[PDB]
Amino acid sequence: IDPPALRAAFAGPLDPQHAEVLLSRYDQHASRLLDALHALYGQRADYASWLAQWLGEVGDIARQRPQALQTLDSTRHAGWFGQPHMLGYSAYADRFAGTLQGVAERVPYLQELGVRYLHLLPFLRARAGDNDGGFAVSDYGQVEPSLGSNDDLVALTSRLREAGISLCADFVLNHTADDHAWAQAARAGDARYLDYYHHFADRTVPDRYEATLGQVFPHTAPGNFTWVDDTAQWMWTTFYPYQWDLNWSNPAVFGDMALAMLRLANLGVEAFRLDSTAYLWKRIGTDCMNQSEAHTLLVALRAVTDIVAPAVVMKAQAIVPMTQLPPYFGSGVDEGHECHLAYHSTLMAAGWSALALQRGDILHNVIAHSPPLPRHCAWLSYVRCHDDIGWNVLQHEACGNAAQPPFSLRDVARFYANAVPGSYARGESFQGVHGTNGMAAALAGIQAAQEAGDAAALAVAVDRLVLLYAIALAMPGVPLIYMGDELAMVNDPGYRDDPHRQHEGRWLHRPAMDWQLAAQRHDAKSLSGTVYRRLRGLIRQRAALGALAADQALASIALNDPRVFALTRGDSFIALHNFSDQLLDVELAAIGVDGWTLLRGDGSIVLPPYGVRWLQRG
Ligand SMILES: OC[C@H]1O[C@@](CO)(O[C@H]2O[C@H](CO)[C@@H](O)[C@H](O)[C@H]2O)[C@@H](O)[C@@H]1O
């Protein structure tokens, strides 16, 4: 290619007043972008032609970036998302406050909680009919009418931004709704857009891929491939049948998606949850996951953002085994130049496992096996979310090692399914071992306690819930609270009586916000008020501990008491966790300390059942 030629295409649509800063960033990241793109599409006859054109469109989008956001681009500090005041909150805009304007009216609630990061679930145009809770996107550039307009989105981000809250939005970049403008163009016979997806005239290729492909909905939707009349072909569909996998091997797809992303950024979104990002690249003979190219694709999108909107962050999802997570942060030449965040799905699943089995040693294993985060990278740590808990990511760990004996994922799954006598949990099986649905409060024993009017059990359960969250709060990066958990909200059986949802078990833990329950957060004596106060405590404390910043180290101290989990941050902070229902103490000699206690140390630390203690070493 011809660098000066490509740079000129990019510049040009730029405003003379901002041309200097942008061209400066373009000069330091462009090469990475170009190398990534070349490895992906360099062999194509129309490469150089597409690049130049595309680059010209990237520059025009760069010019349209509102001044306030450009200023943010220049003032924001790298690794900003990893500061100790960062607290995350995830929820559906509709379940939470009806519309985007309604959500804006609720910002005072988020501010009171201490939220600085707000993830709104899919809110862009979704397929008519069932749209997988918004995950079948029909237009990446338009808010879903029932939720509002693009104007409300902009007004919302401006409101959140002044409250120090960064909007995280889903970029469902692996697949589109089958009614997206592209699928409709494809369905109409437009070969150009038909090529934006994976399509096959026969069952030939599908049969092959299926030989080594796993399944996301083995029961509900063995839909991994679908025959579509309109296109007269088999369409790759990893998820529901109406969600078509995009063909990222086509530069057109890459170019249009990078643009879509930059337009969202321009509307004020600061963080992009790259949904199903492990499935991006398809290659025969492979499970088509975590492929090397998927990573190159991410490096490219990352370069595009470093140049056009550096204040923006990319968060990888990927529900995969531990060894597959860290590479989303970039590898070798590209380490530190891929995703800034990754959901620590292993830590989260390991937490519920540790709780059911009353084994702190399982958490020690996860942390010990958690490699140190690269420069300006961090974890998205969490307790629950809109999805089912995927246990199978803990297979390797379940096998056990020299320090930790084996554990049964099957036993854990049954415990939370309440298919085993004595269980305080009330969840359900989703799709052998696979997944479990249910609210945190429902899994922690709170729902069962309330169900039986047993105050003793309720308190113990509150402890279990707080325990799990204390861990996420002690982690380097963004601890994401799932809507309602701060009030101990329980399951929502309502979907069962709904022909539109009864088929999707995950609705069990996707309730509408209980604002009357929210008002109780004040009555310190109420359950909600109690849970809310305990969490609020840990949040205010973590905000005051520079030792918890993402740049500080994360490690765990090996103990011979299987029930305890000792987590350390930097060299001055240690959090002790008792995952058993038994009172016990941790000897200071077992952690090499002798000091302070957070929101006084001389002798072992006594930890009640399911208790947590934060201490400042020394
Ligand atoms: O069983 C859940 C299955 O789907 C995943 C993909 O990583 O979830 C994300 O993407 C789905 C399809 O777009 C959404 O339905 C889901 O809500 C979203 O979190 C994983 O949770 C898991 O592999």
Image: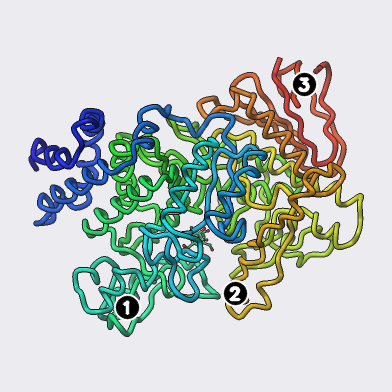
Residue at horizontal 32 percent and vertical 36 percent from the top: 306
In the image, residue 61 sits, relative to residue 501, either above or below, namely above
Q: Which numbered dot is residue 588?
A: 3
Is residue 231 visible in the rendered image? The answer is yes
Q: Look at discs 2 and 3 and give the one toward the viewer.
A: 2
Residue at horizontal 26 percent and vertical 42 percent from the top: 62
- In 3D space, how far apart are the residues under numbered discs 2 and 1 (Cα atoms)? 27 Å
Side (left or right) of 234 relative to 531: left
Please rate how many residues cluster around mark 2, counting C-alpha atoms within 10 Å: few if below 14, some from 14 to 19, many from 20: some
Side (left or right) of 571 relative to 215: right
User: Mark 2: which secondary structure?
Assistant: loop
Quadrant housing the C terminus: top right
The location of residue 556, given as percent across then percent down, is 63, 31
Asked which quadrant contains residue 304, the reply is: top left
User: Mark 3: which secondary structure?
Assistant: helix
Question: Label 2 amino acid?
Answer: Arg
The location of residue 195, given as percent across then percent down, is 23, 68
Question: Label 3 amino acid?
Answer: Leu
- Label located before the other in sequence (2 or 1): 1
Q: Which numbered dot is residue 234?
A: 1
- Residue topped by disc 2: 501
Please rate how many residues cluster around mark 1, counting C-alpha atoms within 10 Å: few if below 14, some from 14 to 19, many from 20: many
The location of residue 586, given as percent across then percent down, is 79, 28
